[PDB]
Length: 21
Length: 21
Length: 29
Length: 28
Image (cartoon, rainbow over all chains, first blue to last red; front, side, top):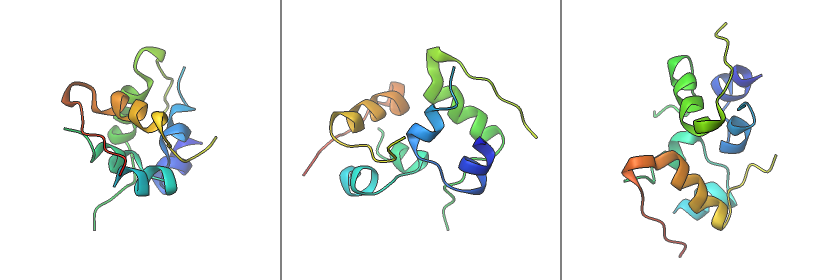
């Protein structure tokens, strides 16, 4: 999920944006 | 530049942001 | 060395920015 | 799913994340 993607690892803008809505 | 960092390569949010102001 | 990781409030706050009008759902664990 | 921000997508990403600071874009 986003923590694994963006906190443990480094995430790109569109990976982040994918968690929107 | 922004093109080496974010297009050729993959930038983090903070790397992208660093190009603001 | 400078940290690229978004954790905690920093991640919420990124979400807040990139999602703008779309909103977002978030759960801190 | 593309990680890479290219071209007019890069300028759009900056539009977004810079908000009221705005930004300087140059391709070179």
